[PDB]
Length: 114
Ligand SMILES: CCn1cc(-c2cccc(C(F)(F)F)c2)c2sc(/C(N)=N/C3CCS(=O)(=O)CC3)cc2c1=O
Image (cartoon, rainbow, N blue to C red; front, top):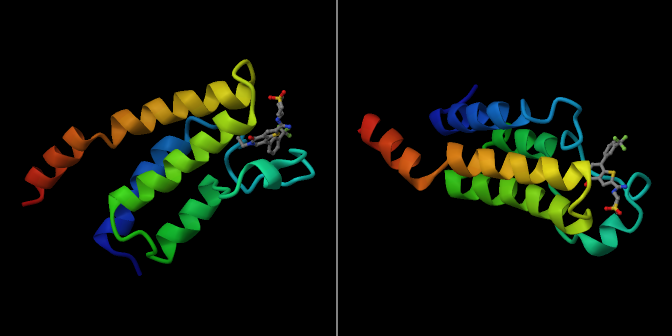
C-alpha cells in the first residue's frame, strides 16, 4: 500500500503530467528518437521514471521530487533549441510546477497538516 508522502507526490505528478497530453515527457528519451541524447544529457528523467520512484517510496521529501522534476525540464531545455515544442513545453511545465510546489504553498500545506 501507500503512504501520505506518496499520495502527495502522486497528486503533484498527476497535475503536472496533464500539461503533456501528447506524452513527450512520459517515458525515457531514446538515442533513436533524439540523436546524441545520451552524450549530451548525463542524467535522463521522465514522468514514468518519477512515478515508479514514487511507487517505490524513493523520494524522502518533496525537495527530492522537485529535483527530478526540474531535471526533466532542464534536460529538455538543454538538448532542444528554444524555438521547439519540446523546449516551450518544458518551460511551461517548469513554470507550472514551480508555482504548484512553491515554498509558500508547501508552508501553507505544512500549516494545514500540523
Ligand atoms: C521532452 C522529452 N523529449 C521527447 C522526445 C520524443 C519522445 C517520444 C516521441 C517523440 C515524437 F514522436 F513526438 F517525436 C518525441 C524528443 S524528440 C527530440 C528531438 N529529436 N529534438 C531535436 C529538435 C530540434 S533541435 O532542437 O534542433 C535539436 C533536437 C527531443 C525530445 C525530448 O526532449
